[PDB]
Image (cartoon, rainbow over all chains, first blue to last red; front, side, top):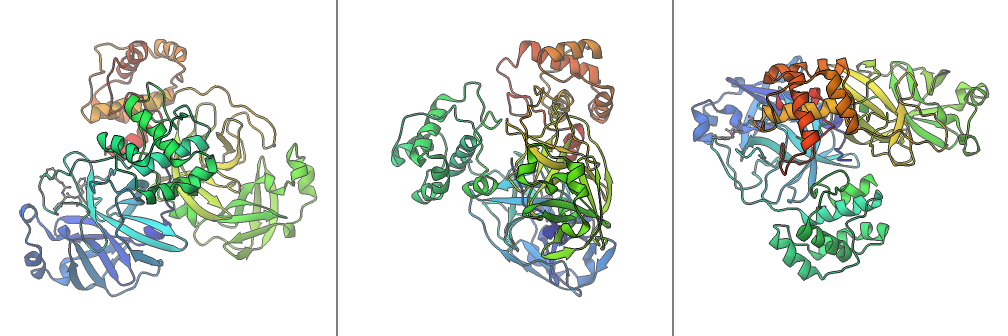
Length: 297
Length: 299
Ligand SMILES: *[C@@H](O)[C@H](C[C@@H]1CCNC1=O)NC(=O)[C@H](CC(C)C)NC(=O)OCc1cccc(F)c1
């Protein structure tokens, strides 16, 4: 049921980028290759890298870019925040229509995990409210990107840079700005306390109804403020009226008003699932947006 | 751990649409052959119980509309192999990957590229249940979508989608047209046997927890494969095969925990329960990660 966008259009952009003894992935659009800047670091550098300093000392030819069997000639380089932009001589014919976007926490995106420029897997993630993502990224995955696809247009929203000690991951948009308070230095970093994406739990509960599962529903009802009071108590995000509007289609399709579902969710939070499960999970799932659930139903 | 699909681009480049009359479903275009479910040739008056051989004799090459996008692919031949249609076309797919057709076993996982009218919608990871059904996400027009695994540069095609059952699960064939399980391609009521838990995958998951340092559940004892299997069946778990034991090898080697020792640890979990304890942050035993999947995400 957890569904990623088809990754073919992105696969045709993935290349390998090497500098010294560091190898990671880059994204090749038109005649520019994007990758994490920490590729220019050495072991010593990575603790407190002075990137502008390290970069000026670098030559176009210190960057080996490989697209499969082929090598691409770097003819220029520049830095945009934490992303290194490498101009090359040849354009990627497989470049798709695209745009660069910075997603809000709570929004989901597909990740194409790559190693040495070769696609390995694809999966769905959500930008957590503390701006980490719960990914499956190992050594060599840096430069893997996250994206959405609308019609024929790929929106790139994420580029992977690091793993925190807790096992979650962090990265930047394609402008090179981190999501969250993180920095691209080799230090143990901790995120803010994470919260649960309420509107997504709600979309998912509706999804469970649509699929014939409704043991958690109740006749009770709640106000929006009183629901948010309980939500905040259990480290759930508050629900905005835009969030309620967005749940509309799902309300309609099932005949369960948003606040009815909020009431059901409130009982779940205060009681628990008591052995029962929902769509197979024993925990409330918060990485399905309303749009995700709709598109798949 | 999360459900992780193979990148779909190599399969995207093979998806086309096949139409008979107003009936449109998806096909798989490899070299100069298009593969699709034979029930594309059915009307509605015909789906209750079709006579496929008699429905086909009446068909000609020029009744088949195959399209890659809006571009027509002319059909120059047609045959029926079990429940799949093979349409020979006048153009060899330039995007044809290295590929093979494999028939998988219950328990094995694969990625599905859910397509509508030949356009990819989404990709996700499915497990073939022991009752030969998959817990998919398919709507109308999704038939002919395929399931695959990728090994090196080679796509192994293992599943083509044909139908949904009363209980909401899905059934289909291999790429040679042979159904998985007892089902037939007819618009009739069909129930799958009782589902059981995929033991080999539960074991892979325990290995996965040990690899990550979560090992409270290992005990000092072992068991025979037969004794484990007889106790497993009493808890609605699948018995283990010799192949299951063999595909657990690498994880056994990685951890130094013999397969039958891990079976004894599971046996004790089944008999005594968790006792309020969690494994990989969960009180449920997960059964949709194969030993190959555990490696993909750990190593
Ligand atoms: C890509 O280059 C790589 C992928 C990471 C590492 C393994 N899983 C992943 O997601 N990134 C890094 O290695 C990154 C480089 C720096 C210069 C940003 N550092 C990192 O992932 O480790 C962070 C860390 C954890 C604990 C303690 C510590 F000091 C640092």
